[PDB]
Image (cartoon, rainbow, N blue to C red):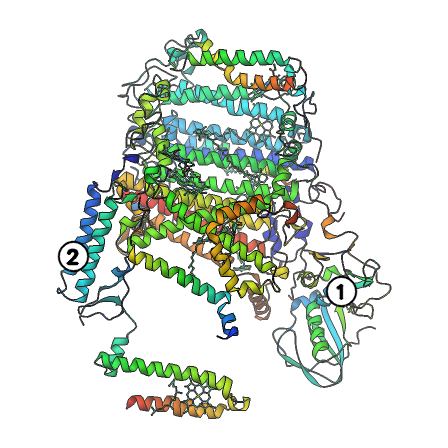
Amino acid sequence: MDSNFLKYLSTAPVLFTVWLSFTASFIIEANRFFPDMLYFPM
Amino acid sequence: DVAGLTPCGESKEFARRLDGSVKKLQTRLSKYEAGTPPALALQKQIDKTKNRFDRYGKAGLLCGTDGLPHLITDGRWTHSGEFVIPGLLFLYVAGWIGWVGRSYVLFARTADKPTEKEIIIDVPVALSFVSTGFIWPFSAFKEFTSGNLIVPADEITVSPR
Amino acid sequence: TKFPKFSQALAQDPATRRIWYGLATAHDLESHDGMTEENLYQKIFASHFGHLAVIFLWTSGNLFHVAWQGNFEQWVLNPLKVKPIAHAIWDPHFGQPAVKAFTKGGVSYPVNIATSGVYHWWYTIGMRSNTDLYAGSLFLLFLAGVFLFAGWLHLQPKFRPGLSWFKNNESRLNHHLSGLFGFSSLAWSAHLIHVAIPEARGQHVCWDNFTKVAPHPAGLQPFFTGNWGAYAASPDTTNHIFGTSEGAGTAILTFLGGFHPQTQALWLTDIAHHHLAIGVVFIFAGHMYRTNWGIGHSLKEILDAHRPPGGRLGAGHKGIFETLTNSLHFQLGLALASLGVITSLVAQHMYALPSYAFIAKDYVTQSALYTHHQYIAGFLMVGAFAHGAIFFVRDYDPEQNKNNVLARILDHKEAIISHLSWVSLFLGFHTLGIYVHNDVVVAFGTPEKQILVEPVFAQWIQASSGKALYGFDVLLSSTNSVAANASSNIWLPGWLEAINSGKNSLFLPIGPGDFLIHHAIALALHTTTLILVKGALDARGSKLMPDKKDFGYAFPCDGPGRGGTCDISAWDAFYLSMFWMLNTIGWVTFYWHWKHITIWQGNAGQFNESSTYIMGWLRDYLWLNSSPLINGYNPFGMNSLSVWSWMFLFGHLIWATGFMFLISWRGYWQELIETLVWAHERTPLANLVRWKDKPVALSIVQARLVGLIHFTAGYIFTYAAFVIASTTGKFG
Amino acid sequence: TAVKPSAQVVWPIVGQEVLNGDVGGGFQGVQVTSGFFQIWRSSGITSEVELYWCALAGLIMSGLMIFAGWFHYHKAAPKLEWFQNAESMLNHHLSGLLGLGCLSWAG
Amino acid sequence: ETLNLQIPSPTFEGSTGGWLRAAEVEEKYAITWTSPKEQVFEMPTGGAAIMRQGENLLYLARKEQCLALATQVKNSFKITDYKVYRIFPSGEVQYLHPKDGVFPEKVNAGRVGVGNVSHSIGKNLNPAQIKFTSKSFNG
Amino acid sequence: SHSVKVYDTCIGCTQCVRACPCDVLEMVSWDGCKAGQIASAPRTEDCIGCKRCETACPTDFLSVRVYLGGETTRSMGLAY
Amino acid sequence: MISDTQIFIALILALVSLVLAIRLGRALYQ
Amino acid sequence: FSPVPSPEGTKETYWETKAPSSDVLGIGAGVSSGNFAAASVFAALVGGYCTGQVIPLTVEPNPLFLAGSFLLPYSWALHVAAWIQKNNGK
Ligand code: CLA
Ligand code: CLA
Ligand code: CLA
Ligand code: CLA
Ligand code: CLA
Ligand SMILES: CC1=CCCC(C)(C)[C@H]1/C=C/C(C)=C/C=C/C(C)=C/C=C/C=C(C)/C=C/C=C(C)/C=C/C1=C(C)CCCC1(C)C
Ligand SMILES: CC1=CCCC(C)(C)[C@H]1/C=C/C(C)=C/C=C/C(C)=C/C=C/C=C(C)/C=C/C=C(C)/C=C/C1=C(C)CCCC1(C)C
Ligand SMILES: CC1=C(C/C=C(\C)CCC[C@H](C)CCC[C@H](C)CCCC(C)C)C(=O)c2ccccc2C1=O
């Protein structure tokens, strides 16, 4: 894959948008399978 | 119980919360036919609402006079799952993010163009750092005691006063 | 060309800026041309007498207007049903419906109902008729004149004190503790024992009969025997009707604790014994310092000796004595910080422990008094930090303060400022985060997913004082405790009755809504402190302006270079913290008033459920209680809440006009004014008239001050109109 | 007159499916106020099948415009004397764009 | 040296941006310059004027207005022949710029330094030290 | 008028003098810097306080310092 | 109730305060 | 800014030694460290005893036990004076 295109995807706004979309996405998935967790179950 | 609170499993106001929440959904369900997509959507919401109320009742949460769960955060172990353990979980992630971010800013200082490493992140090296964060409490304290976390006051720029 | 006679730099300005700046600098005597230190202290001395007379004239007018136009005598007969009158209205802009709508209070003329509580204070301390209200007004008119003459007299050449007098720290402290604080607390104990307590028991005691009416039947014989407890015998019964002889005791010095059951106020014999005890303690305190007879302390010696030997404070307080004595701004800051805390204690302890009879059934007076004194507190607290900033810029000498507590503060100012920055952000992220979580979770129909933290630490403190509401069974709440057994023969029985009735405001029940707002109030206290501390500690210099102290306290900026330096002065951090002070007192008074109006209705559960999200504050407090206020006039008529309805809109108008001075800045306005100057000169019949002062746009600093004043004035008028009209309209 | 227009349906995640209100017609969704339904009836759409063809027609146009922006910057960029033809541009934007736009829409 | 009041003025059609009553009762500023051409320039107070070939003369209300024109006349028309005068209503004409025949950014002998402080800016005196004293903060 | 000061950290770059819109500053001879020249403020009665000189100055802390003072017709930049 | 003569006593004493306030203000003004 | 006055008999009390000079003790500058230490324990015992005897406070408290109870905080200042004198060789 082109190294200048990979250097473009390594730029701060793309990584910030991708990482926080990935981060938001597994919070969303964790609340789909395991909803309404007000407390650590113990 | 604690602070004059009632366990949610025997609170009558918690019981009325669950019933009112389901009556509100059932009257919306009364306007749809059985196999329709709006009927299945609301029937799945009545199942979810009942499950949540059942779980809260059996969890050891304490309800108020208002029938809502209240959190006890004074440090007692019977209630550590409401703040102390979520907090221990948080600080592990937070220190991980902090240790990993700190490790990359120190790497980028030794670069050919240090400010280009911060707007164009060296993703293989930055991923090398994110994996290292799992033992940040040991790595950061050894960093502290080996004189590499804290810089002395006389290498820090301060205002004249 | 001669108005700023104290400033030749302003008196030679040819613009309209001279009039504005001369008015705004008039009281800053230190900056006036040719000011010596002798004259600075002598003008402050006289203008303190002049301020004192203004306070006595303000008080005499309140007494006079109530004696003349009030219904004090009718109110005294039936104090829970009559609404006290402040003064009458004579306004030729009124219509005849307005004249009728304001003719309440049992009188035949338009009047303003009083929210100040002066009726309850004057009743409790003894006043019964209009003729002793007027006698008090006459005394204050005399006292104002005596202090006006004293101010003029101590400006005369022989009566002007020397700087050695003004800086006698030990003699002034001895007299202010033992005489101004202590003896007058003792003299106020005498007034209650001789006048207020007898007239609370039906017996009139005035100048006419005081020397022949004994406060106690035994009478100054138990005092000279050590049988002091004979003065606590037969306290007022719980059947006592205040102002009358029925149910009355003979005691003058008691420690019963709790409230008089009918007035719902502290016992007058507890209050007299409070002032006797406080007065004795203060008189002893006023013997601490050495003046002329060889006993006592040198203040300089105490400060020099308090350097901890571990060396963690450096040189300690060596040289603080000279720094505080020579800096009036350092003295002012200590006084304002101390005064600011007290006026906050006054607001907190007067709603929970009221001393005046039948007040705390005056929901409007109780609300206005709290709101008034917390706002005074926030202003005093800002001023202390502002004058601490003025101290560092102007009066602080780093070479007379080598390695002090003061110099070592400035040595780790970034440690202090960054840790305020962290704690503000720490509080702000999570306090706002929980509230937004609760709002979103409640909006989606799931209020049981709210994060509701029980404020157990405060509930445990309530229980430690005997509150039997949370089952904590600790200290005073515990029946068999060393704490509970110790106070049992004195105030414990009366206090437990007072704190375990849900009929007063002593240690009000708290829950998750109270937890959340206290952490918001904590956020606002640390953030206001941050701006003010950053203003004080960066006042002398920073990295942008390392020579910031050469420019003063209030300067506009250092220009657009070095990135831009708008709001870089220490004054500008006063400016910025004023918004945060207004925000915090808003959060405090919004909380106090909503918690009280819901309790006064009998619906404390409405606060309990709706305070945990922000829409509950918006609809159940601001929107719900707005309706009596905004209906003070409408196309269907008007009532006596029409004035507050107008002040409400008036306050929104002043507040918004302040935005114009804060958002739009000078360059736009100076260029308009140049087009207006052109048009006047070119307009026939109008260019016959010429300005003496060239019209100019307001200065950069002045516009900040003008916008801040408009913002602040709009803030006060709006809330006062709301807190008074919503409480009046509801009566609950 | 009875059904409320709605063209946005939310996923059930954190209780947010309360936003799928009863807009009518055996349907749950977010009520939309942009007036597209009234446009489509004015256009004579009358079925979801034709709405899919309009959606494809937009996508093909969307691809053609991004191609033209690339093409006219990187492959075939007009010279300044092309852009400085104000009489030609006005003739075409009055006659061709606005005039044939109205005439075709009238048809 | 003195302003020759008879020097022709650049062709201008007038504007509302010119000087007001304060120029005829307090002070007025004038700028003269030599132009090799009859060319359009921009007035500091408004629109465009045309400077005549040869010697031009303007009157402005502010000293900064004369120098803002001087900057423009030297940056776009390469005229460095500009002399700025101050004129009082008493008739007194005060030569201003360049003050000694040489531009300020070029050094000249016989210029005495005003405002020069022998130490760096951080060596000033603290305000408390010079309180109730006439002593200056620059050491 | 405004008070304009030049400190002996001036490197003689003449940039303040070129940036001054009111001809307040000029260059005088010196021997304390390599350039042999220092900025001077002989005409501060004409200083309007714009601080364009301070912006132009490249020494770490400004060799030229403007201190805004009493306002006049000249220093308020009034054409009226 | 308050008589008008009593109001007039207050106006006399407040007038005495106005005269003393002027003199204190003139002394402060110098 | 002008001379700040202090009462006559003001002396210098700033110390950087192990213990302050005995001048910080005022009228007790000549008392021995043994005498403060014995007074310190005596005031602590008598003050605690008098305090203990009136913990349930009545409307008739013994005035000697009240006055004697003020010896407990006074003992704190006594052992500080005992430490100061011992470290000054008194
Ligand atoms: C009849 C001729 C004609 C037409 C229709 C247009 C149309 C347009 N020109 Mg113009 N243009 C023309 C001739 C024409 N031009 C000439 C001769 C010149 C040289 C002087 C220019 C120079 C020029 C410049 C410099 C710019 C335009 C721009 C635009 C667009 C304006 C934004 C807009 O409303 O688009 C939305 C409206 C639409 C209707 C979208 C339609 C898209 C296609 C291209 C329209 C034509 C399709 C086709 C002819 C129809 C086939 C019908 C068939 C089914 C029967 C628009 C597409 C501007 C622009 O946005 O650039 C992209 C712009 O910056 N034009
Ligand atoms: C991971 C990097 C990192 C680390 C270790 C720190 C460390 C610290 N910061 Mg933070 N800070 C950072 C990034 C970082 N900062 C960024 C990016 C900003 C801009 C928003 C700030 C803004 C900031 C302020 C305004 C304040 C601090 C404060 C502090 C101190 C206390 C902790 C705190 O308040 O956190 C607070 C953290 C934030 C407010 C923002 C953090 C935002 C993200 C989560 C961190 C950045 C992640 C980064 C992209 C890492 C990528 C790594 C990858 C390339 C391998 C501590 C010195 C406070 C202080 O001085 O108190 C003593 C303080 O007041 N910082
Ligand atoms: C016993 C002798 C004595 C007394 C009574 C005073 C009294 C006073 N002096 Mg002092 N003074 C004295 C000796 C004395 N002085 C000596 C010996 C010296 C020379 C060494 C000075 C030098 C001196 C200076 C230089 C100044 C004063 C000033 C003042 C006035 C202070 C302002 C004021 O009214 O505060 C009144 C304060 C109180 C009544 C106590 C404070 C109360 C606190 C804040 C809380 C109270 C709460 C309580 C519940 C109140 C309830 C109110 C009610 C509505 C419920 C005050 C009248 C100042 C002044 O104003 O000059 C005119 C001033 O500038 N004095
Ligand atoms: C609602 C109005 C509001 C809000 C929220 C703030 C918030 C804040 N102010 Mg400001 N301020 C305001 C009005 C406001 N101010 C006004 C009117 C003034 C008068 C001019 C000031 C003057 C002022 C000064 C002078 C100071 C502050 C400070 C602060 C901070 C104090 C609270 C804190 O430390 O943590 C609270 C933190 C927050 C509220 C941040 C919110 C978290 C965000 C929303 C996360 C959301 C991320 C999200 C995905 C973004 C989406 C973007 C989208 C395009 C994708 C904070 C950043 C102080 C400061 O910065 O100290 C550190 C400070 O010194 N403020
Ligand atoms: C700097 C943060 C901060 C600040 C300024 C305050 C301030 C306040 N709190 Mg809050 N509080 C905080 C953090 C904070 N709290 C946290 C993190 C908790 C645990 C959930 C609480 C729990 C709490 C309760 C239960 C109550 C208060 C109350 C109050 C008020 C009275 C004083 C008090 O009890 O202090 C409390 C002080 C502390 C708990 C000390 C916190 C200091 C550390 C540095 C904060 C961070 C700890 C960290 C996150 C946890 C460690 C890890 C752990 C999970 C293993 C006051 C408004 C009381 C009140 O009046 O409410 C109406 C009350 O009853 N607070
Ligand atoms: C802000 C301010 C500025 C400078 C500093 C400062 C001084 C310290 C400060 C103070 C300001 C202060 C303290 C201001 C104080 C202002 C005051 C007290 C003003 C009082 C005015 C009273 C009047 C005019 C009443 C007059 C009555 C009359 C004429 C009745 C007369 C009569 C009637 C009918 C009946 C009787 C017979 C006669 C005689 C015929
Ligand atoms: C900016 C500036 C620059 C330099 C100069 C400057 C002017 C000095 C400065 C200004 C500084 C300023 C403006 C400073 C402001 C400082 C302030 C407002 C300090 C507040 C102090 C309150 C305290 C210590 C309360 C203590 C209560 C206690 C111990 C209660 C205890 C308890 C009791 C008795 C009863 C209940 C149980 C418990 C809880 C046990
Ligand atoms: C509106 C506005 C003006 C124009 C306002 C001017 C020029 C003031 C005109 C006010 C009139 C002439 C008097 C107002 C009268 C006051 C209501 C009462 C003042 C008198 C008391 C103080 C005694 C500015 O000059 C300005 C400057 C910098 C930033 C923002 C602004 C800004 O917003």
Say which quadrant the C terminus of chain C sits in.
Answer: top left
Secondary structure under badge 1?
loop
Q: Which numbered marker is on residue F13? A: 1
Q: Is residue C60 left or right of residue E104?
A: left
Chain letter, disc 2 residue = B
On the image, the x and y values in percent for residue C182 come to 51, 22
Task: State whether residue C681 is above or below residue C270.
Answer: below
On the image, the x and y values in percent for residue A33 come to 29, 57
Taking depth in this image into account, of D100 and B66 the one nearest to the observer is B66
Q: How crowded is mark 1: few (under 14 residues within 10 Å), some or many (20 or more)?
A: some
The furthest residue to the right: E110
Secondary structure under badge 2?
helix
Task: State whether residue E97 is above or below residue H71.
Answer: below
> The residue under label 1 is which amino acid type?
Cys
Residue F55, quarter of the rendered image: bottom right
Residue D97, quarter of the rendered image: bottom left
Q: Residues within 10 Å of mark 2 (few under 14, many from 20)?
A: some
Taking depth in this image into account, of C152 and F71 the one nearest to the observer is F71
> The residue under label 2 is which amino acid type?
Gln
Q: Name the residue under label 2.
A: B26
Chain letter, disc 1 residue = F
Task: State whether residue A18 is above or below residue C46.
Answer: below
Q: Can residue B100 be seen in this view?
A: yes
Q: Is residue C655 left or right of residue F37?
A: left
User: What residue sits 49% from the left and 13% below the top?
Assistant: H47
Q: Which numbered marker is on residue C7? A: none
User: What residue sits 50% from the left and 59% below the top?
Assistant: B128
Q: Distance between the residues labelled 2 and 1?
A: 83 Å
Q: Is residue C711 visible?
A: no
Q: Is residue C685 left or right of residue C113?
A: right
